[PDB]
Length: 120
Image 1: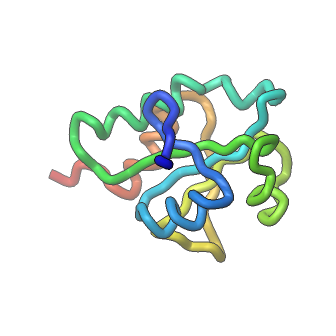
Image 2: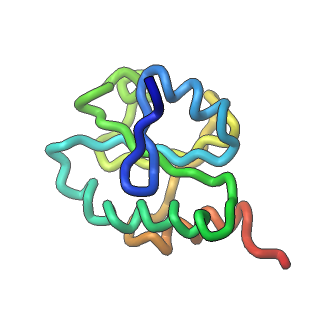
């Protein structure tokens, strides 16, 4: 039907993954579960980094997945427990990068700025 979203970020699945990756160059995605406890410490922080672009118009977007709902892309990648964040660049499917942060929206834009930045 249509790609649903959450607050300011989107969600991924067994059908949106292969698409969102090869559809948007900058696309963030994290694997977590409804029972996880450290997967919500930045729920409003991981969504604020996606609104910082709404005022500009960049093409960077973040996403999240329910390892308990899909569990089809997490078992294939061999995740190592939640929360598990991952960054895809225009569909990589080979050697994606990993987020070394996890504290607030700033940590999300800080890693995203390394690829965009102002450079005015």
